[PDB]
Amino acid sequence: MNVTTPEVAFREYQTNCLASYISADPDITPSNLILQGYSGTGKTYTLKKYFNANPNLHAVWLEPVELVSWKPLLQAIARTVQYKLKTLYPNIPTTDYDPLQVEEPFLLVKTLHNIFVQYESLQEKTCLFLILDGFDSLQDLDAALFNKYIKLNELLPKDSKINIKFIYTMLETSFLQRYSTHCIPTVMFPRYNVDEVSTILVMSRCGELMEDSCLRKRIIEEQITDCTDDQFQNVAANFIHLIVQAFHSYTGNDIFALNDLIDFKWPKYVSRITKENIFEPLALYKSAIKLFLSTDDNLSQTYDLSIISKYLLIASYICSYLEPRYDASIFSRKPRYLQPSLFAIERLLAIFQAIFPSLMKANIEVFQNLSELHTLKLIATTMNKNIDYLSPKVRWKVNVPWEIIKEISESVHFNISDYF
Amino acid sequence: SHVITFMTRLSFTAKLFIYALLNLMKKNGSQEQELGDIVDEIKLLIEVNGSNKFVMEIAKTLFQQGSDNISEQLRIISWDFVLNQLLDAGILFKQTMKNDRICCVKLNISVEEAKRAMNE
Amino acid sequence: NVRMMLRRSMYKLYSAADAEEYDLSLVENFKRLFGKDLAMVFNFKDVDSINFNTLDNFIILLKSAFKYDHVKISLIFNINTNLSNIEKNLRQSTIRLLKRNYHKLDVSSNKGF
Amino acid sequence: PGFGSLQRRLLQQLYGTLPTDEKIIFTYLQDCQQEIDRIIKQSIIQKESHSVILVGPRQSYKTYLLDYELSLLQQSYKEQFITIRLNGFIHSEQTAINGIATQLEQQLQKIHGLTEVFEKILLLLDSTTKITVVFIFDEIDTFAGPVRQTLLYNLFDMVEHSRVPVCIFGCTTKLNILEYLEKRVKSRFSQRVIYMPQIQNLDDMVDAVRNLLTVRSEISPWVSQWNETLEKELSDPRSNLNRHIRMNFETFRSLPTLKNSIIPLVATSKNFGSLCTAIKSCSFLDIYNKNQLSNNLTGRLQSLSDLELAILISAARVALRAKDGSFNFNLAYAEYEKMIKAINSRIPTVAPIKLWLKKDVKNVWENLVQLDFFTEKSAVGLRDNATAAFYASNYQFQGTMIPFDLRSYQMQIILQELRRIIPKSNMYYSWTQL
Amino acid sequence: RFDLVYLVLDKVDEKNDRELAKHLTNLYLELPVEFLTMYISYAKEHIHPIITEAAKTELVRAYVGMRKMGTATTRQLESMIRLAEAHAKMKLKNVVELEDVQEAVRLIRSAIKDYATDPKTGKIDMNLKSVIQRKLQEDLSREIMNVLKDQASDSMSFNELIKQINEIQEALSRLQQEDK
Ligand SMILES: Nc1ncnc2c1ncn2[C@@H]1O[C@H](COP(=O)(O)OP(=O)(O)OP(=O)(O)O)[C@@H](O)[C@H]1O
Ligand SMILES: Nc1ncnc2c1ncn2[C@@H]1O[C@H](COP(=O)(O)OP(=O)(O)OP(=O)(O)O)[C@@H](O)[C@H]1O
């Protein structure tokens, strides 16, 4: 049977290309297929939409994202196909092989050959497509892994009724280019243009917020009798166009990023709607001006620290950015963009004593505050495993940026800016 | 050697790549060359010729495929395919870094036989 | 690493489920295995020392659980200093997941005398 | 509507899945095909042990020929040959031994309706005959693991002692195969290396195209119209459809790669009446051609926003000034801050352009690392093997711990390429140079 | 600000050594200066050439071409007229010809040796059969075989053929060797 093509917009080359490598005749379709495109390019959405328009096909959907390593990936193929064949052909008396016995790719070929023999009495060769969404998204991945799936079909008995027509999707480009000489039939997705992103969210997210709880409470509160669902869509649609124009340079040409600001700012945007905001979005924009002027993606006196604590951090930044050459020149009475350098603990205490407002000395409280900063992670150490502070080889560095320390010195009345 | 019989039958892309690499070797006085330098010298050697229509057609076929309107590739067409083909045949040895323009391309074959094949 | 996080989380989940009367398939199979809905509460006992690169990946890993209808997840964050440390190390794509439904609480002993 | 039957025949013919009675061998391949045909039949019919390696690049119709001869032998010599298949990627040296035994048992059962393991192949045959074993291998060189090559070292040894004749073939793209086949294995191998012939003239390619695109079966009356129109577009060297092939020929001379684009053109075809309009001009390989290039460096660069581009340009400027070519977020914003000041400064003042905050740039900064414009200072990238990747997934590098604003990056696009690609209508075009 | 800079290099070539050596070695065995000075004084006395419209426009493309390859300051544009007038004065033509313009530009190019200079780092080629020579000859030969027969004649004059394609002798000689 021939394949009907879907109507997916902004992908009207791939939806027609897959009519080539996917067909009811297993003697035509290739043994490997790659769909390549970045995140938010619709590869998962396009492939699933096409399959749901042709129910006569038989396919298995898996996700390497959940299948953390390759061992689950092999096992899921064996397990799902074993179930899927039963679902397709319940009348055939068949036996079972344990899908948990898969340890190496050879065993998959062994198990698959054993399974396919049971279906030798089938009327016709059966074309089967195995689908993995985001192949290169696998958490533990290597170059040699993909070659293991490319040449798998020809190790099967070529007279077998069941043919495994693998399907893969890839995100990156530095991964796919290593396999260019194989000339695997490839269909491509580029990044979406600004115009398409605006239209996609208009078509997708309009119906989502037309029926949210927040507005229909406010509409009754504002007693909007003339409101209609056609107005309801355009009211929500205006929010998408404004937020895109406001934050396209912020988010990018991304659909995932925009789909969250449309969520957070929406209740606050809902609040400013009144009886006078029904018909003029310009006034509604004026009321909600402060929403757009800030991203509000931020999660929200920034650091409650003791007097001893404040001078401890101030002294450390000097150590991490001033050369040891200048320690005697500046403090004795005798680079903002670079990453901080390491320093020794003796350097910190000497400078801390040197600038503290006769000597301050180092009691338990000074060390008690110093260790807390390490616990608070405002100062880092040179280790990651089995932290031992008293080991002499560990060094220290500053984890606090310049802007925070600027405001700390203000509450201290210590003029750091004159030391550089 | 029988290797030269296969060298002489390579596509134009392979011959140009090998010739540019050899010229960069003779300029640098070293064998391995930075991968970005190779694709820069390819453009240098392509455009050092005159603006004659034959040169223009060759350059358009090489860099932007000679397509109708869609164009402006940063590197020549099949620049990866022929690189892998030389790499997978054992002639060309390259180290692995995901940064394209800091990896070194190194030859396995003798210094003389490449020129000998190119001189044929 | 993410591999360790998924296994250990399922190991504890199965052990508690064993007292009713190691991967995400256990989450899918949970209602068929034990006949009850599952509500998971994750307690990040010390957020600061956690490798954010591992944690950022793991949060996305847990996001696949929303396909199931019988599973509900809650996250508890032990924050020592302020929200600012989270806003730096975490990828800004991840943060938009947390902000959709969150509650901000202070539990320090010192509070206005 | 009914033309699809001929279209199916065309699609099946393009894929090489025609029956052996109709399988086509190109003239430039026929010379080596007859040598392969001779050795196989001599080893089977005359019962002589032999060993040969086929050598050529990938996508070179190399293992295709081995299928062709065996597919023909099956039509008349079902009882004469035994085939064993192995591959260097899937079948590891641990699982290689069981791979032969399982496949050997399958063939032995259907025919009738640990050094001794190698000998037991002959013992099973001899006990049931009182049939030449055709070994076929892919990626011969790949078996050069630390474990001894007894997987192959014993097979070439069997050539000397096989009471039932043993013949061995293999595929490999290296020209240095004898480096992988060590001296101990070399002493037993017949060393009949056959480097595959190459495509070296446009006549070879066009005739090979003629071999694929000819229809020599009277399935439908439009077959003659197909062959008429086909040779119309190949009789004139300056044809619109032939224009692509010559350009294909000069760029790369691997025939299957050319087929990769032609099949979509055949597959996208809807009906014979509309097929005539498209096949001549052949404007659908141009769209496919740019499709291959849509996600390259140029393709990614075109879809960015102005702010993403502006930070990218400033990021490149730091890289160009820096001898190492490295930069970080702080330097990128500083040049972004200065360039906004410069643009604002060159404006008449007021008689009585926003600098984005350092927080909001973070999302803009993340997009550029995803899209591979930036890369880490020492980014090794993808590993080659799972064991090597195991160490990578466990080790924690410096970049995973240092702050988000101080991770050193490098650039994939040089400012010169920016100035070559960025539209001159862009406001930051004037900032492309220093 | 110098108009012309000349890079005179001496190479150790046995062939070129004999060419120079035999010139000098026989000269010390065993136009005159009076005419030469008479010529120069005559040329300076009379000719005051004026640049024509056609010669003017070609300077723009000549200077821009060096400009985009960058040290091509506007100083070298003075040489693009100063040398042009001096060539016409030698020609005794009372206007500056376009041939004078292009030859002077070539002279500046040859004096500085741009064709033998690296556009990237400014280094000089020591040597100043190649595959690019092959393809250009191949492509030229392919088109000649068509144009020679595309016209409604079996053959045509080579002078007209050159102007038809240049807008060659070796390529056609090879075809004659192959009897094409
Ligand atoms: N043509 C389109 N029309 C409408 N919506 C679209 C279109 N293309 C993409 N989308 C939307 O964009 C979303 C992008 O997410 P998608 O399913 O493609 O993830 P993905 O790229 O496979 O994921 P990952 O990056 O995690 O591997 C889709 O879920 C869909 O809602
Ligand atoms: N049984 C077959 N039927 C039809 N076409 C086939 C068959 N086997 C291979 N091909 C053809 O072979 C081409 C792919 O390259 P091929 O299989 O010849 O390489 P190979 O010999 O495996 O290469 P390598 O040197 O990498 O081992 C495709 O064009 C495909 O149509």
Image (cartoon, rainbow, N blue to C red):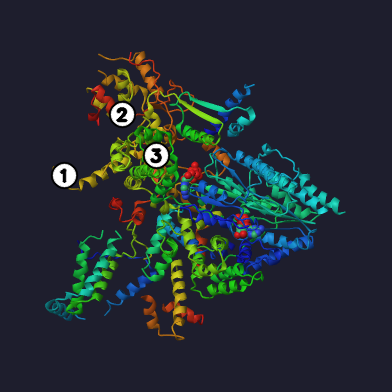
> Foreground residue, A344 or D79?
D79
Q: Position of residue C23 (x, y in %)?
A: 59, 33
Whole-angstrom CA distance, mark 1 to mark 3, is 37 Å
> Foreground residue, E103 or E124?
E103
Which numbered tag is attached to residue A300?
A: none
Q: Secondary structure at mark 2?
A: helix
- Mark 2: give few (<14), some (14-19) or many (20+) Cα within 10 Å: few
- Mark 3: give few (<14), some (14-19) or many (20+) Cα within 10 Å: some
Q: Could you tell me which chain the residue with mark 2 belongs to?
A: A
Q: Which residue is mark 2?
A: A404
Q: Which residue is mark 3?
A: A262
Whole-angstrom CA distance, mark 1 to mark 2, is 35 Å
Where is the N terminus of chain D found, in terms of image quarters?
Answer: bottom right
Residue A386 versus residue D130 in the image, above or below: above
Q: Residue furthest toward the left?
A: E45
Left or right: E37 in relation to D357: left
Amino acid marked by disc 1: Val
